[PDB]
Length: 80
Length: 80
Image (tube, rainbow over all chains, first blue to last red; front, side, top):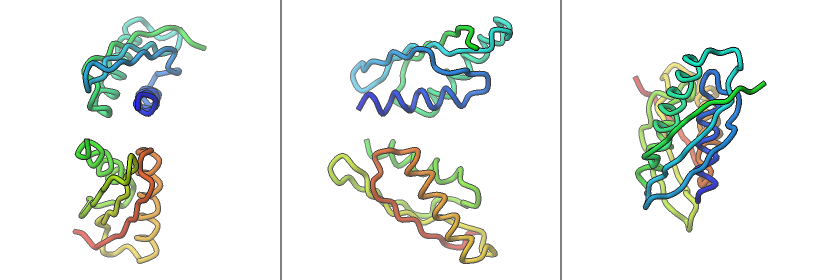
């Protein structure tokens, strides 16, 4: 069900260089498709540009691995 | 559906050191669970012991990644 998909999303995101955990993930079904919004932790000393790059890389990785996701927004917050 | 799960099984198996493609995969639902049997290609010059190790590693990798699989047999054949 949903929990299995959420596990996969978290595991996929964590394997992306520069992710320091998944801080938040909201996933919902729109029909058979998942729409999700996520916040990742990142090094506080990364630049804003780097954090944007990490978010883009997470979006690509997660959407590539979990084919039912049809919308994924990823934002970042500083995390030790 | 099934095709999405089969894609995941093949992709997981291919990422295991020493797999030279998935030659065969039969997957079936027993209730909500998947039972599967797979043949991987391996280097003809690997030993029988090494081929057994690769099969064990595929079983572990695939079962670890695809939680609905409750039975997976993996065998090997020589592949160029």
